[PDB]
Image (cartoon, rainbow over all chains, first blue to last red):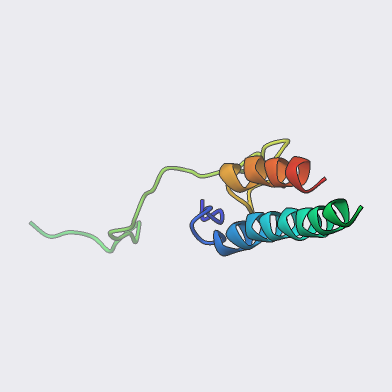
Length: 38
Length: 49
């Protein structure tokens, strides 16, 4: 049939994984800051 | 020869193989999205969580 291939919707996955990457980095930046402050 | 009046009017027609129902598969609701999207949705879900 004409089922939507992954190529058709492949930017929502990069964004998703990219946001997860950014999210972890932001969390670790907060952690590192407070950890050094201690 | 001298034919009589036609006792059967006919012509050239078109014959095709008789079709039928397409018996939609049990799991035919996942067609709108390819198999890889479905597999990669589970992966993305397990990763976001």
